[PDB]
Amino acid sequence: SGFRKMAFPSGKVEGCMVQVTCGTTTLNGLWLDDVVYCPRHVICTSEDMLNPNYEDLLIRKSNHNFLVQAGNVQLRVIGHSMQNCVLKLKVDTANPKTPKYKFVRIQPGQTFSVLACYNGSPSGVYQCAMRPNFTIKGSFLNGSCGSVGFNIDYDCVSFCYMHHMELPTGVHAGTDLEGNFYGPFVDRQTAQAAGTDTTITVNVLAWLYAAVINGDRWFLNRFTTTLNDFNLVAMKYNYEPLTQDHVDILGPLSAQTGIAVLDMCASLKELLQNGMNGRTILGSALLEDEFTPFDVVRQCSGVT
Amino acid sequence: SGFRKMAFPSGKVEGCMVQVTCGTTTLNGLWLDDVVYCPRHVICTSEDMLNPNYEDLLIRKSNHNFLVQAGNVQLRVIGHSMQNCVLKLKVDTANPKTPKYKFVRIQPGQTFSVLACYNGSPSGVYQCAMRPNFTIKGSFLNGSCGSVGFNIDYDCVSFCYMHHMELPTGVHAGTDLEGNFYGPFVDRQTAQAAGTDTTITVNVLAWLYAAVINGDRWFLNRFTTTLNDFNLVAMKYNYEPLTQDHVDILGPLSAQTGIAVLDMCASLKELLQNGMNGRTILGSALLEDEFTPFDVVRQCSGVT
Ligand SMILES: CNCc1c[nH]c2ccc(F)cc12
Ligand SMILES: CNCc1c[nH]c2ccc(F)cc12
Image (cartoon, rainbow over the protein chains, first blue to last red):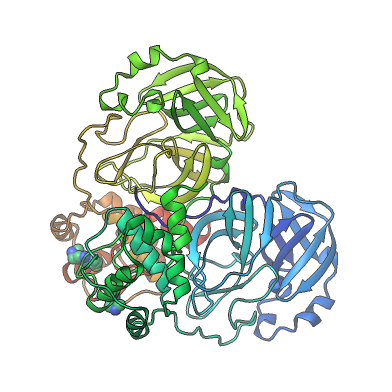
């Protein structure tokens, strides 16, 4: 028993982190096979970031200008190319620690682990979610760019995020490993405001199921609701609309606990309308939305 | 910017996890050098756990009864001994992945990362604290015993916890790597109730400093207090008494923010007396106490 915000074990990803320096900028790179992936803004000076023309800046860079260091040993760069907002630096050595991997572009509401790195060295690992406004609420200081987000399924690492920037509001924006930003964000130091940060309703319901499984049941009530009735309340509280796909995904949790999805929606509806009255659920005084139904099943079953 | 409950990168510890089976019980072991450490209750059947005589049960076990598997390869056990509540299984092969390590016995209030494992395979990593009642609030299912807690200082892993049991209240108890339980707990399936779970005051103050650094400042007030005045309020709310040692440890955070420790205590005093009024601090509606002052400095400075 017990339910924690758990990250995937990070070892497989730690073996892929390298330091990339171009001119006076140093950030992190991800070394998989004979390619090092890093944010293209490694070629920028803080001044260039105001209005960078990446194709123009890249013409002034050659293979020898990209310094790639794995631990204390230098990698030889034999090619470089820009794909969207990432640079792909071809090196002469395949990473011996390359795990089985995929590049995936996640949907908002999905969770992943971030291995925060500085100078190619891992500092910590935490779990987060792609917010519905395509930002993430991470913990990233200067030098953390190029740190990656990932999920692990047995022995295959699915990389989904690479860190690029912090908006002036302290939230984070990045790309998938193809270099495409999540959301409308651009790698320029300009006014970029995030949209509404709505709550991931299906994740809140999954976490309420996790609470019931782990013994926290005070919030269960005698009511039920419909998808349309629940959604009138979800809209009012800036919660994402719940669809039948979300109800289907919650099926296994509904079956395990014996609590119908719409009954759990009615509990959530009363929590939204009345608050927690100074009570807590799974050690939280807020309705937690960074656990997917898959995360709840995995943690409650012990998937390794 | 941003502040997350961050765990240490777990790779160094993942390379130490093995599966230990004795009879029909399978749990995790920690392989460092040529020794595998695991809870001594690996020799028990669920029935033995009611009133186990470990010395008597161990006489019926020989080296060949301890099956140790690292990945898919078997380790040869050439010796075994019991030290307090852990068994030390001497194997014929030193773990090639043994990192630089120490065994430390932590104090209540200190934090560490747990690599939850099942069948010797890592499932996830999370951060927690040794509670003042010597329990931890983890996420452990059956098969997780032998999972370890640790801290990392550059390249040295300090192991501080090994998981042994879950109390009937869903909280967790374990030992240091010398096999001595934290608190009064025993490895027997009997009535063991935890004492008061007080709040780690110095950690709450550290987290309020982290909030100020990261932009959450609404709770700062025009007041100050004294250690004795603050402690009258801390006692009332089941908070640990704050000492001058705690004030000294908060010195660097006080210096960085320019907010005197006793002024932050006065903010905390008003938060205890008035609540948050539906507001949040660092994405929490509760006063977070599982970040030490060292954790705040580390995360706010980017230690790798
Ligand atoms: C969601 N609107 C009411 C509200 C504000 N804050 C909250 C925290 C928890 C909860 F269950 C409800 C609330
Ligand atoms: C600590 N006693 C009041 C109280 C109950 N619950 C709380 C949650 C947050 C906070 F700042 C204060 C409170």
